[PDB]
Amino acid sequence: GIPAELRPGTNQFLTTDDDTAAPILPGFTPTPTIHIPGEVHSLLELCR
Amino acid sequence: GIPAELRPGTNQFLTTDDDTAAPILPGFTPTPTIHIPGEVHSLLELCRVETILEVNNTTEATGLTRLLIPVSSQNKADELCAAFMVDPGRIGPWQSTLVGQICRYYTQWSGSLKVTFMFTGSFMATGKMLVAYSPPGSAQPANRETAMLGTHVIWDFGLQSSVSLVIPWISNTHFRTAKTYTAGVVTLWYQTNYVVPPETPGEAYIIAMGADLYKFTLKICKDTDEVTQ
Amino acid sequence: GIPAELRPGTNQFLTTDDDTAAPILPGFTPTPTIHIPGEVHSLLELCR
Amino acid sequence: AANIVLAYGEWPEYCPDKPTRPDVSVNRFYTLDSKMWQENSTGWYWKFPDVLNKTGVFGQNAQFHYLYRSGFCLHVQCNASKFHQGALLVAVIPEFVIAGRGGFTTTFPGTTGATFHDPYVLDSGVPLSQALIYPHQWINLRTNNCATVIVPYINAVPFDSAINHSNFGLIVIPVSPLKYSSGATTAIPITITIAPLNSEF
Amino acid sequence: AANIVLAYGEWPEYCPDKPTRPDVSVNRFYTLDSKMWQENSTGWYWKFPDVLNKTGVFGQNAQFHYLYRSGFCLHVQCNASKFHQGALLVAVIPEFVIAGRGGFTTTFPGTTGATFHDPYVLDSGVPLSQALIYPHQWINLRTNNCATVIVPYINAVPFDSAINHSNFGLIVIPVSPLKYSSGATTAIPITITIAPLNSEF
Amino acid sequence: VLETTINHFFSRSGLVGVVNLTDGGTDTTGYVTWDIDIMGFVQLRRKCEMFTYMRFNAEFTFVTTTKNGEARPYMLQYMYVPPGAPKPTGRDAFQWQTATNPSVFVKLTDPPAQVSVPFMSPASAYQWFYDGYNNMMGTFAVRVVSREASQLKLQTRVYMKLKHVRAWVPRPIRSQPYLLKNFPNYDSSKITNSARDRSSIKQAN
Amino acid sequence: VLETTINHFFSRSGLVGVVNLTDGGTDTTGYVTWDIDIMGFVQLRRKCEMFTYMRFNAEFTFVTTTKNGEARPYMLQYMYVPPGAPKPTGRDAFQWQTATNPSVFVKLTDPPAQVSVPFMSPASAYQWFYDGYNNMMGTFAVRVVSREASQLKLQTRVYMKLKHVRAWVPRPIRSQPYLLKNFPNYDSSKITNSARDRSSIKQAN
C-alpha cells in the first residue's frame, strides 16, 4: 500500500476540532427549507 | 478504503520535526498586526552592530574602568600599550559584545571582523599610536619593529580622533577538526610619547569596539555555557 | 477523515527498503560541494 | 553642523486612520534644568512622556486625553573648554525599566530625572557594553559637544495613557570620567531640549 | 620524448574565486639529492609540500602563509647503461599515511626522503599489486629511463597549512631488483625534479 | 544563512515545564493546572528578553508517564482554559464540562497529543518589558476520566514550540543572574562581570 | 549495470553497533551513549577505506528489546548530541532538557524509530586518511522516561544506512588484518599474503 507514518496528535479527540463524521443514515433527504422571515446571521444583528 | 502500510518512524515524537498541529481554537482571528519600527529578520543584523570590547579585564579594574584602555604621558616611545586576542567565541574581552554573546549559540563561525578605536583626550593633546594585527600561528610581536613588519595602521589621534582596523579572516575549525587554537592578536604600540600642553591632564583612555562584517556567518545551533539553570 | 485500511507489510522494518526518514536537524544547510578530481561513479571504473 | 540619528530609520508620522493635532505653543522647544557633571558622577536618565507631564501647555494636554501619541526631537548639548576631556554615551531605550537592587520615583523621576547606582549594569541588570544596539550618539569633548536623536512613536498599540505608561527613556552615561587640570571649571553643564513631533491626543 | 601522465586528468588551475601568485624564482626547477639504488634496496618515498619546506624561496613562502595551494610537475630520471636491467614503479599517493609496524620522521622525512621497510605492503598495510590505481608510470631500463607526472591540487578544502599537513606523497619502489654483470657500476642514481604549478599563498 | 533567521532561532520544541498528577481519591486533588509561561526555565527566557516585542503561535505536546513509567489504557483530559476564564476548582468540578474551554481526550497508551494555540493578545504583540502600571496566554488542566478515582501517579512533560515568530526592538543580553521570575532584579552587592580576568592587559595569551 | 554504482554499493542498511541499557536506579547509570562511528565493525570499514573522500547522509533505525525480548509500554528518549556539544552525564542530568539537542520520544512497543542525519562536516567531505596533525558526526543517548527508575534491561541495535554517497580518489583494498581502530597498523612480523600458495608455478590446477 501507500507507505505512511503516524504523527503525534493521533487518536485524540479534540472537542473543538473541525472534521467530518460518518453520516449514520445516508441517502436520507431531510425536509427541504422554506422561507421563514427574520433569519439571523450574526449576534451583532441582535446587539444593535 | 485506501490500502496503506505503516512505516518505521510511526508514532514517534521528534522534537525538531516540522509539522502541523490541530488548531485548538479555530475560527478565532487574532489581533491584526500594525507597523512597529525596528523589526529584526536575522541575528546577523545584530552581530554587525559594533559594541564595546572590555579590554581592561583584570582583578584590578571594577566598574566602567574595565572598558577603558589606559594611556598616559608617562610611557616611552616604542613600548606596548595593550594587546588582546581576536576570538569572538572564546573567553576574553569579546565576552561583552553581541558577537561574543551570539557566537555562544553556534558551534562554528567564520568571516571578517571590524575593530574600531575611539580616543578621548584633551582637544589639544597629540601623539601617534601603532595599531597592528598579527595573524594566527604567530605569537604577539616582541617589539614595535616586528609589529611594523606586518599588517598595521599608523594612527595619530592629534588629527583623526578614531581609527577602524579590519581583521581579514577568522574561523573556528581545527580545534574541532583535530578533535575528530590561536587565531589573531591585536596590539597597541606607542609610536611617540603622548604629548601634552601645559595645564591639561595628560592621561586619556582608548575605547575598543568590535563588529562583524557582512561576510561573517554562523552555523550549528547550540546552547550557551553562561546560563546556570 | 479519509477512510483507509491497513495492509500486510505494516509496521515492518525492511533493511533494504527505500524510503524517507524524518530529517532530524531541518533547516541545516551542509557545507556545499567543491570540485575534487577523480570522482568515481561505478565500480566498473575500478575493475578496468 | 548637522549630524542626526533617526531611531530605527523612520520619521515620526501621524497615525494611519477624531484626535487633535495641536501646534501653536504645543510643539516647540522645551529646555530642562541643566545637569552639572563632575569627576565622580554616575550619569542620568529621563522618562518620556513623563518628564513633560507637568510642563507648559503639553503637560495640560498630557493631562486628561487618556489616549496619547507623538514622536520627539531630542538635542543634547555640553559646554566645555578645550581643556576638558571626557565622553558621554547618549542612548534611547524603549520600555526602559529600572529594577530593584535587592519605587515610583525610580519609575517616574519627573522633570529633574534620576541618577544611576550601578551604571555598568544600567541598573537593569544588563551590560552597558552592549547598550550600543540602541539609537545612540557619542558626545566626545574632543570633537562634538552636541548630539541629536529623532525618535518616532514606538509602541505595540496605536495609543496609550501618557500618565500611567512611559514609552521609553533617555540616558546620558559618562563612559570616560571628566578630567581637567586644576583651575578649570570643575563641573560641566549638560543641556536637554525636547521638541515634540506629530503629537496627538 | 614526451610521455606525460596527468593525474586524474585535470590540469592544475588557480582557485575559483587576495592570495599571492608569485612566479619569478618561485616556480622553477628544484632538483634533489640523487638516490643511489642497489641490488638490495627497498625503495623510497617523499612527502609534499613537506620536502620543500626548507628550500629556495618557496620554503620561505611555505613559511608563514598559513593558507597554501599549488600543483606540481614531477620528473624522475635514471641514468643506467644498456647492461643494467630492472624496473621502477613511480606512483603518487594522495594522503599517503605511514603506519606503525607494531614518528614525525616517518610522517615528515624532509628533503632526503625515507625508505620502506615492507614495500610489499607499502608500509600502509596495503597490497602493492594494487598500487596501480594511482597516477603512475613505469620506469623500465629496457625502454624508458625517465617518467613525468603532473599532479593537480587535490584536497577536500581549497586551502590548508603546508607545515602541518602533507597533501600527498611520491613513491619509487623497484619491482624487479637491479641486476648487472660484474664490472658495471654497482649503484644507479635516481634524480628527482619538482616544478611547482599555480602556487598560491 | 538560514539558521540565523529569527524564525529558525526560536524553533526546535523543548520542555517548558513539568507537573505531577496523582489520583488519591479524596486525599489528593486528582488533577493539576499549569499556567502557560514561557519564562519558567532560563534558557529561552534569556532569549525572549533579547527583544522588546514578539508575536507567534504556540504548539504544545504532552509526554506523560506513570512513576516507573509503564503505560496502561487510561483516559486523560487536557482542557485549555482561555485567559479570563475560571480554572477547575476540583477533580469533578463543573468547569471540566464547560464547552468554551476546549478539551482533548486521549488514551494514555497513545502517542502524545499536540495542540496549537494562536496569538492571544489584545495588543498587537507580546511585550516582556512594560514600564508603567502580564501577557496571559492561558492554562492547561489535566485529570483522569473515570467515575471512580483510579489510584495512579502521573507526571506530564509539556514540550512547547513557537511558530511564525516576529520580533522588534532588540535588547542587550542579560549579564546578571536572574533573582526571581517576572522582574529583572539583580544583586547589587555582588555583580558578575561580562568577561573573565587575565594577568596583565599587555599580555594576550 | 545498476548494482555497480557507488550509491547502490553503500546502500542496504545494516547493524553499526549495539549498546546495552539497564535501569538499576542508583547502581546502574540507567542510560547509554553511543558515539557515531562507521568503522566499528570491519565489513563496511574495509569498504570505506577504499576511497579517500566521501560525502553522504546517514539514516538510522533503533531496534530495542528487553532481555528475553518481550515488549511492554515504556517510553524511551533518543537524543542526538551534535558535534561539539556536551553529552549527558547522568540519567536525569540537565542535558536531556537541552533543546538544541534534538530528541525523539517513542513507546517501546511501537515500530522502530528512524532518523536522518545530514552531512555534518565543516570540510567539503569526510576523509578517513589525513596525513598530518576525526570526522565527528555526533552521538546518541538513550534513557527511559519516568519519574521513578523502572527496573529494566535493554539492548538497542543501531541500523544505519547511507544515502546520496559520493566518493573520490579510490584506494587499494587492505590485505592485512586490522590491529586497532582509527589507525592502519599491521603486524610487521607476520604478514598475510594476497593469494594462497600452490605446488609449482608450472602447474595450474
Image (cartoon, coloured by chain):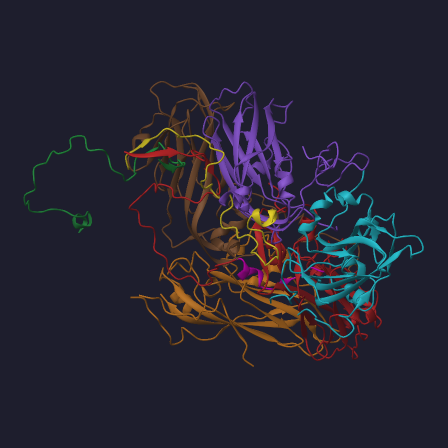
Chain colours: A green, B red, C yellow, D orange, E cyan, F brown, G purple
Image quarter for residue A34?
A: top left
Image quarter for residue D200?
A: bottom left
Q: Residue furthest right?
A: E183
x, y (%) of residue G50? 64, 45
Report the quarter where the N terminus of chain C lies.
Answer: top left
E1 and B64: which is toward the camera: E1
Q: Is residue E191 visible?
A: yes
Residue E68 vertical placement versus G85 (above, below):
below
x, y (%) of residue F39? 50, 44
Residue G145 vertical placement versus E98 (above, below):
above
B66 and D114: which is toward the camera: B66
B136 and C13: which is toward the camera: C13
x, y (%) of residue B64? 68, 60
Q: Is residue B49 left or right of residue E22?
A: left
x, y (%) of residue G54? 60, 48
Residue D94 vertical placement versus G172 (above, below):
below
Is residue G67 on the magenta stretch?
Answer: no
Image quarter for residue B34?
A: bottom left
In magenta, the rendered stretch is B43-55
Q: Is residue C29 left or right of residue E153?
A: left
E178 and G75: which is toward the camera: E178
